[PDB]
Image 1 (cartoon, rainbow, N blue to C red):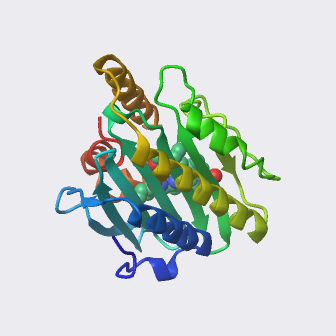
Image 2 (image 1 turned 90 degrees about the vertical axis):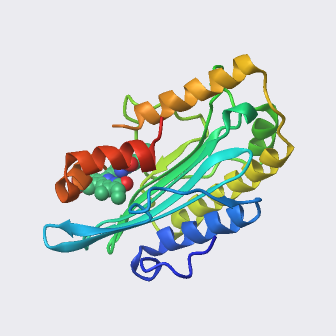
Length: 238
Ligand SMILES: C=CC1=C(C)/C(=C/c2[nH]c(/C=C3N=C(/C=C4\NC(=O)C(C)=C4C=C)C(C)=C\3CCC(=O)O)c(CCC(=O)O)c2C)NC1=O
């Protein structure tokens, strides 16, 4: 796992670069194994109205995380994207870590991050709540409203338009905190019963189903069949 061979990192919005480096630093601490995507989908290049569209996908796995995906994209000249999900192995009942940034050369327009509950409770595990509790509330001046296809998200979800670099740094630090808690608990987690495993797996199907609400730009560049394969095999496999 390493981003030093990325062709995109040097032209991506700096908060995106920061967050990618922070996710890498986190994941490098896990016993990562490679996760194979379709051969053509590791590195994607096309055109979107005459401007280069480029996507780099990196995917890993652990016994606790079925699929760890980091996507970076430059979707023509005025859109940069980071999308990251860690899909937990449902046997372990961990929450879904997710984060997305949408940016341009002018700055960041949306940043979101959560540890999303898989538990039919919609609660996070006790150890997460206690560790999260001791961090305290970060302050944000523009918090955005979740569409109806929330709250597959948790109470700790941040969904914002950063107002200045201090908010960019605060957003990234909260993701670094989320990851420190998450990785640590993954190392300590024990297999659930079959019943609760299936419960968690359904929470994961529902989370991926809901998130089908990105397509449009991919359809525009690649068509609808390519887009629907990408959504169902790369992004949000069910
Ligand atoms: C390479 C793939 C890819 C493309 C081409 C892409 C495009 C894309 N994402 C957008 C926004 C967005 N996209 C998301 C979020 C997500 N999007 C997701 O696929 C997931 C899983 C989330 C997480 C919830 C959010 C929250 C916005 C808000 C737009 C903004 O406020 O800037 C917009 C709005 C810009 C506009 O139309 O004016 C475009 C064009 N996003 C992509 O990921």
